[PDB]
Image (tube, rainbow, N blue to C red; front, side, top):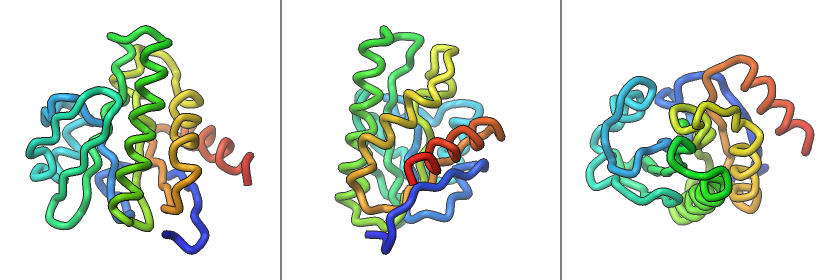
Length: 163
Ligand SMILES: [Cl-]
């Protein structure tokens, strides 16, 4: 575990993380993907061997000895708000179990279902609160990776407001 388990947020490419493992905001088919998706694939392509896993689950594949945790958040384009919310909470619970099983002291994580899978809605608070529900009981240092300065500010404020 980390000596003083913390949350931090960084506004940068998760492919350049400084943590002991990475959560890929995965598709269920283990497909390399397109756009910002390809970043994780480009950095750790070996981790996409047999990475396919259902919505609401997480599957870890090693790239060398570096764990890539494929976490499949729901695509809110396909799910009702209610069922998408359930699967989003479940995907993070499976991430907490994987991070624990791996025995890492740190994990880089994105806000699942807030990008291409957001169904065009702002899910910062929804996704972050499910992340906290799952990871609060883990002792890894959690570093949340985002794209936009405003999201960095809002994630930072939500973290600091509990400390
Ligand atoms: Cl997404």
